[PDB]
Amino acid sequence: KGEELFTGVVPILVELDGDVNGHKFSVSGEGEGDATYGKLTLKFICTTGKLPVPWPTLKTTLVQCFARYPDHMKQHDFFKSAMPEGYVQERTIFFKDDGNYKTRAEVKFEGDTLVNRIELKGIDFKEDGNILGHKLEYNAISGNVNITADKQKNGIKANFKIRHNIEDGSVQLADHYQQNTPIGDGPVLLPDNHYLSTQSKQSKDPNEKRDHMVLLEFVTAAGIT
Ligand SMILES: [Ca+2]
Ligand SMILES: [Ca+2]
Ligand code: NA
């Protein structure tokens, strides 16, 4: 039943409240997802002024229900199966030689809109590290989300690495651990091991003077032949 809600273009809303080393900020995002093509287009705005961390570090936090699951893998799509009641998505993101983000999000339909509502808490950051020092490039992010069933929670777990380019040519590693739990009581699809091949490009709206990020993202399930 969940999978039927994604056969067309779906409007997306993202709302994030954050506190990173006591820097409090909010982010509002809008756009649309077409799961048939694994395609997401979004624009995010910092509504509190200047974002106190680099946009790239927030990208993974700011809707894996928009993944293109190949037909032969459709029985492994936990994300859409939880809809419309939705799922809780939790992460710890460990920035190597720096702080961590912990995130708790509720992803669900509000009428015909897919909504991602997030709380983000960041601690242990260095004031002149790559995050609070704003030393990261703004360009593109890709990786493979490794998913396994979590039957004890009627949900999934995932892990993956992101390598953020630093302006010196080096990389800032962000190790991600993830847990998803259904909000509702409907049955969900507990998957075999597989991965999401995910890539996005970050850009700027030439007309936009607010602190913002434009994103074009493609997400495809794989790793079952
Ligand atoms: Ca940035
Ligand atoms: Ca380079
Ligand atoms: Na679609």
Image: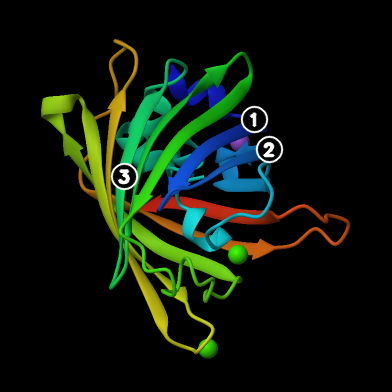
Q: Residues within 10 Å of mark 1 (few under 14, many from 20)?
A: some
Q: Quadrant of residue 157?
A: top left
Q: Is residue 21 above or below residue 173?
A: above
Q: Is residue 34 left or right of residue 129?
A: right
Count of residue discs? 3
Does the beta carbon of the residue at mark 1 sit less than 8 Å from ligand 3? Answer: yes
Q: Quadrant location of ligand 1?
A: bottom right
| Quadrant of the frame with the C terminus | bottom left
- Numbered badge on residue 91: 3
* Closer-to-camera residue (149/174): 174
Residue behind mark 2: 30
Q: Amino acid at mark 1?
A: Val
**Residue 149: image x %, image y %?**
19, 37
Q: Earlier in the sequence, mark 2 or mark 1?
A: 1
**Res 25 visible:** yes
Q: Is residue 218 left or right of residue 20?
A: right
- Numbered badge on residue 10: 1
Q: Point out the frontmost of discs 1 and 3.
A: 3
Under circle 3, the secondary element is strand
Q: Amino acid at mark 3?
A: Arg
Q: Earlier in the sequence, mark 1 or mark 3?
A: 1
Under circle 1, the secondary element is strand
Query: Label 1, label 3: how many angstroms apart (C-alpha)?
Result: 25 Å
Query: Label 2, label 1: how many angstroms apart (C-alpha)?
Result: 11 Å
Does the beta carbon of the residue at mark 3 sit less than 8 Å from ligand 1? Answer: no
